[PDB]
Image (cartoon, rainbow, N blue to C red):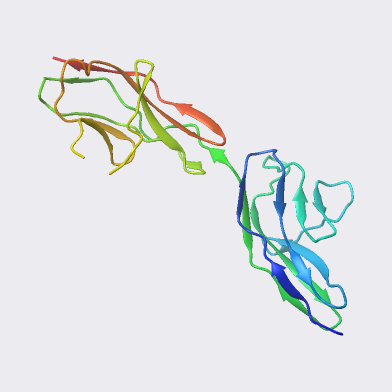
Length: 198
């Protein structure tokens, strides 16, 4: 008959590793067949073809064969599609496409610490900012301290997101500690700090 455009599948938020491919969907319905147009941060995405890098499939999907985030190209942003035709038009949800990142400077790194048995020790670790959220693990002399868990009155435990806390300091606790952060982008390491039990 003569149905006005409808959006049957909205594009969804997406995080991608730099230079990897990416796809934002736009399943449209309408009679006449609606024409689909894409927008990035309010401006129309000059695509379809031409000597560029953003492609638009027949199903209206926006395809980045290689997602870019450099000085020249920056695909990061808010995207959305509009379906039109003689009778009307429909708009899709605005989805956000962003390239994973991992700032490489620690907010705070642990520093050498001395402490007497029984006393309480605290090693600082402020992992650098990253998206996705970076993961933070502690390593003592090459052996990763496996307590990457969460909520019991254990011995050594992480606190304030990133800081290592040792309640009753024994002598075995002596050693070199360092914390590591990581997400899709890669890995980030703080230098080694020595914990001395006097």
